[PDB]
Each structure stands twice: as structure tokens, then as C-alpha cells.
Image (cartoon, rainbow over all chains, first blue to last red; front, top):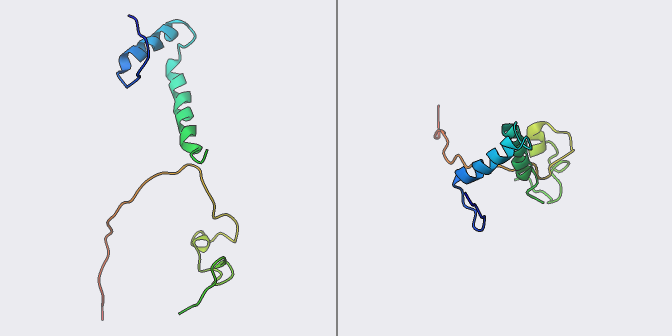
Length: 51
Length: 51
């Protein structure tokens, strides 16, 4: 697909698909892991509110 | 009827504190990692009297 991002709003799929593109890309694979990282990233978002 | 000066309890009624509530000597009382909304808004509590 095309998937132009212009007004991101959930709908995973696409994203996931990108994810896969990455996942596939080997520039992601433990994509999952990344989500952890991300989780953490998020989490750190959680952690810096004050920032 | 303990009269108390704002900007001290950690002395003013020294150990009558949140710090105390930790025990917490006279360190912390701070901000702000993470943060985390909960307002469990009910309690289980009682009523007057037991004599």
C-alpha cells in the first residue's frame, strides 16, 4: 500500500505493516523488542512529565 | 489545636508528616517520576462509636 501519514490515528495495521517492513528490513526483527523499548520509551514519557 | 507554621512540619510537629508517614527522616518530598492518576474514591470506613 501506500501509506502516507498525514493524520495518524490508530489503525494499527498500517503501522504494523511498516513495522513489518522494518521487521522484514532486519532494521527491526525483534520489533517486538523495540516495542519494549518503546514501552520503556513510552514509559519514559511517563517518567518525564514534568518535562 | 497545634498551631503550625507553614514551611515546616518536619520540625514543627516534626514527625507529624508525610515524611514521617514514610518515616523518612527529613529528606525528599518532591516531584515527579512517574505520576499516575488514581482516585479510588471510596473507602471502606466506619462510623462513630464503639463503646
